[PDB]
Length: 5
Length: 332
Ligand SMILES: COC[C@H]1Cn2cc(-c3nc(Nc4ccnn4C)ncc3C)nc2C(=O)N1Cc1ccc(F)c(F)c1
Image (cartoon, rainbow over all chains, first blue to last red):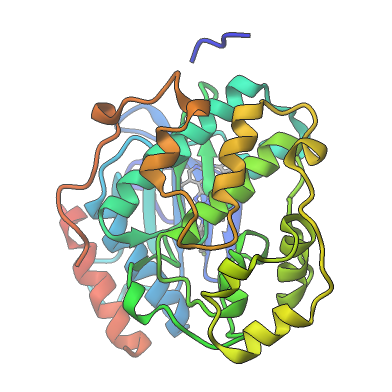
């Protein structure tokens, strides 16, 4: 998981 | 009555306090929805003091992770002023509402904690203590931007006058109180806020308050139930006899391991939690160290974690006068 904020 | 009519209409309820109400409304000028807090505090001295300290702080602070004041609506004279309306950016929810139903990914916990500490670095750099950090005071929008709000209990830090006796009455939210509040502290040092952030981190990991004390001393007993008995070195700081002897009277307990309470948590998050939830406030991690912790490595950038440009160095009738003066800049 590497969420784009 | 929600009298913000010159340019603000279509009001929808959000929440309330002992002396006010927060609503959402359409801004006919900027063509965006905003939040408006109707504040009616003038009949109670406590309500007035909290309103004034908050307006003074929020108008001076300017930070992405702290709610700002965009406008203030009130009558043109003290005589006619019964209510004060504070206009702010609209935030879709808060961390309390979010944690009631939503599991957070590790990335969300990391980014939310980073923003909390980023805002807190600014607050502390102005020599101000928030003193009521908790999930409902952390506003969130749909893009996961976080802003700290509710500075009604805020104070300028005063470590020289922090000492008090055992069982001294305290106003801020019970579940987020550091152990020393119940022992020997007035909550006038920066370490008070770090403890609350540690409680918030634990709550983000499990969706439940870590220390849900039901009354004043039960709070200390929940804390010690997890941290275990304070060490001899930490008892060295507790010199007031009633507090010391209370702790010595308790049966021995060993520490509950963080990895047993939070088995699905990132090990680096638990190492930072341990440092925030340190019993001895003198050994507890400070906000700049917490930002530099390995858990926050993907976000840490001290050049992009600004500090304040300068430190922040009465009857209800007189407090009303000061609220009028403080809000004057918003009159046309
Ligand atoms: C009722 O609020 C309580 C608390 C939290 N809070 C939330 C917000 C706030 N909430 C949203 N949105 C939002 C959140 C959740 N869902 N939504 C939709 N957006 C913008 C803002 C500024 N402001 C405040 C605030 O000042 N306090 C303090 C306070 C003290 C005394 C009072 F009398 C008082 F009325 C309010």
